[PDB]
Image (tube, coloured by chain):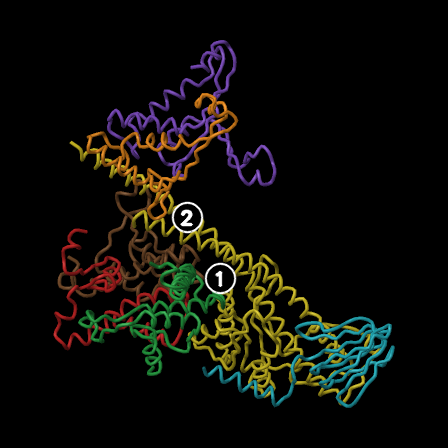
Chain colours: A red, B orange, C green, D brown, E yellow, F cyan, G purple
Amino acid sequence: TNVISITDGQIFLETNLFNAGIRPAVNPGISVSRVGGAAQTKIMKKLSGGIRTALAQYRELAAFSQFASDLDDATRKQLDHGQKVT
Amino acid sequence: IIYDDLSKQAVAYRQISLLLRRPPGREAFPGDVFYLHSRLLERAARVNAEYVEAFTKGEVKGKTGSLTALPIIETQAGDVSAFVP
Amino acid sequence: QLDPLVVGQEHYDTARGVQSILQRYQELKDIIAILGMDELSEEDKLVVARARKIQRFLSQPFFVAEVFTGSPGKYVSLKDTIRGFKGIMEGEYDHLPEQAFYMVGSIEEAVEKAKKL
Amino acid sequence: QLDPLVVGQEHYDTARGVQSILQRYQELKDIIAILGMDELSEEDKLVVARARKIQRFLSQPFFVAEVFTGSPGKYVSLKDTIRGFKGIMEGEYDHLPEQAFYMVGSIEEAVEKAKKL
Amino acid sequence: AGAKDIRSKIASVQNTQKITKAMEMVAASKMRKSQDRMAASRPYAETMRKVIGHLAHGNLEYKHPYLEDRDVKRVGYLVVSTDRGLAGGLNINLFKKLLAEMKTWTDKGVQADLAMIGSKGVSFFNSVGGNVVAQVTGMGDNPSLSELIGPVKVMLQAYDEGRLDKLYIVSNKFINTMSQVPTISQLLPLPASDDDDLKHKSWDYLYEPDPKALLDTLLRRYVESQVYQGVVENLASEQAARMVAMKAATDNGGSLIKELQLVYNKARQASITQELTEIVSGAA
Amino acid sequence: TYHLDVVSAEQQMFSGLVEKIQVTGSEGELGIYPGHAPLLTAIKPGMIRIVKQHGHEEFIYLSGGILEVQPGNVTVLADTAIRGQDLDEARAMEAKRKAEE
Amino acid sequence: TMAEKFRDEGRDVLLFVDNIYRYTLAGTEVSALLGRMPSAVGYQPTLAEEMGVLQERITSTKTGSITSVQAVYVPADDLTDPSPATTFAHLDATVVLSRQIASLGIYPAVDPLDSTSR
């Protein structure tokens, strides 16, 4: 909790991701950079913005719609993009 | 009588007690923190007419006196298992 | 300062209405994972629809955060944000997609975003 | 030492396959606990059936445990075990019962034990 | 993990357990209403079978495609499924039994053919790739015969057009409040139900316009009647299956509360001991 | 008087003992007096007239169905919706359309 | 000690303790005032001894006996906490009183399924 308070950001590595094949196991939802895109080349800046937000919200849809065992068209399109970028 | 925060009296008593080097107990409150609120609140009473007459040397005879108390406490996250609550 | 007297009933009843919907959504949200929306009722389906779109309309882009986002910052006046939340509260413009409420700022831009998509 | 360069790709890929299946089975246990297995997806039932077979095929008779099991002990070579796990993951054994995999040295012994039920 | 979030899990699971208890109570009540609707479906089919028996087994017996017997070169099934989950294995057990017989006929070279009631069976046989020509879906807890007319008209049309040779309905049976079973029963050609009488001499019908057209309408109405009876029994079997599933869910939720509370209380006690050790060892 | 039942597959519309009725058969009108002859015919959509025993005259609409008669017991097997080979063929095509989807 | 006198006169005696939990907590507070190191979930180190010193005087002797009926409060509803865990070592019988049985109007409101005796 001290070093999280001092630093400019956090990469969180998770064993549940590392065990499910997701190596490197960075958790997108809980990891942040306090400078962000101001430290990117501008090409990467465009592409990056879409990817992070789509992944974290895809995580919500995947939990919701699996136990519900359910489908809707835009949600389906979103979900199988989110799995493909993941 | 309304005591607006008995939680803030326990915290003030904890502060002053630790600065006097008294041994701490659970949640660092001193050992006698129950005796603090217990002797406070048990003064809130109804007293019969014979007590009033004896106290006031007969200047009042028929009436029964009382003091009702509404202490306030603040819980954290709805936890009632904390020491003071 | 969220007192009916000062803020006027206009603001107070709008705020308490939003708060009451979002608490009802949080109660449903857990058992929705068990029930989906299939076994939820029609009374629930309107409330969740209003709640999600209200919870999108609470977002805003900041002039500071254009660095992070590329989108320009927005400013929204008190009267306008009351009009927008009461507009979903009473007007219930579920005509519009859920992202039409998100990061837009003003009520007019929210409908215009839905007019564009 | 579990690196593609040190152990080769087939070993590495079989070990990551076993972990991936067994982790996914852990993710299913909470819904299985509350609702039971009939509410799983039709390939989630297949993962659970392979994961339980993998769990049992990790078990092995030891020569020092004859005082306990009484069963004769077994030595399994590396080539033989990776072939067994790869074959279960490809599903070439998906018609044997779980009990056939318990306390058997090699996959052969599992098909032989399934012949004895 | 962390006792403040563990206590959050406990409250979430407790809330979940109350709602499943409510769903058990509702499922039992809906089972009762759907088994009253089941008894009302009997009299229409029973009297229609007596009339068909009077014509078919009386001396005035005719030839008709639905009464005549032929060797199977293609086979059809009507199949009933739920629109809703939480029914346990009711659909899957029925579909497994169907897959065995559908395999057995097709090994004889018979092309199988399917009509689906309810969307679960539609989704399953689309994943299996079964040959489905018609469906109706979203009847929910209010089935109606006039919705069933489509898919049975297709299968009837293929039967007298000679593209089907035997037609089953595949459905569960509400044998009891406590127990139900998946079944496959042949509705065409007409089963040789004995229905033996001589009292037809004593009142014999005036055929207006003609006997054969009347007999075709009876056979068509009778098939529709049997399909609707199967659907209503499968709906009552759904409600009884959801009832027993929700009972098991409520008990498994309560049994998980009693384990999480041991984890929480052990973490509560350990946190007090560790903090008070740091305090007492912190002085001096 | 005779025991009449008017039934459909979903519900039983009416029943009881009856003095007479008037019914639109496939070929024409028919009156069932006490102890009428055995009969089988299809009946047309419309109102049918009941007079229950003790003379309580009534109208029941039926969407069609089958009539049968025999002297002691009589029944009508009513359809719920208008039945036509063309309309049912249209439903059969509708059913296929869903299968494609 | 008053019950010990009536026992020594040869009677059979009942001792009611209005809360045994408040004896335990009084022993904790005194132990903290004396400054002894705490134990377990912050209880005194002498917890099991001080309970034993009370409960072992309450017995049947060859002259008379003291039976005891003790009200018990369970902290946090937790039967694993040292105060319940220490007390239940000494109890022989256990009577549970129910709000539901009182709601039925049945009195005394003992619960027959959770009340037990060894």
Q: Residues within 10 Å of mark 1 (few under 14, many from 20)?
A: many
Q: Which residue is mark 1?
A: E88
Q: Position of residue E29 (x, y in %)?
A: 59, 60
Question: Mark 2 to mark 1: distance in Å?
Answer: 23 Å
Residues marked 2 and 1, same chain: yes
Name the residue nearer the viewer: F55 or B8: B8
Report the amino acid beneath label 2.
Answer: Ile
Name the residue nearer the viewer: G65 or E125: G65
**Picture quadrant of residue A43:** bottom left
Q: Position of residue E163 (x, y in %)?
A: 55, 86
Q: Would residue A25 be seen by someone viewing this image from the given angle?
A: no
Report the amino acid beneath label 1.
Answer: Gly
Residue G118 against residue E58 in the figure, above or below: above
Query: Left or right: where does residue A38 sit relative to residue E144?
Result: left
SS at circle 1: loop
Question: Residue shown at 49%/9% (left/top)?
Answer: G9
The image's mark for residue E257 is 2
Tag 2–tag 1 contact (CB < 8 Å): no
Residue A15 against residue C101 in the figure, above or below: above
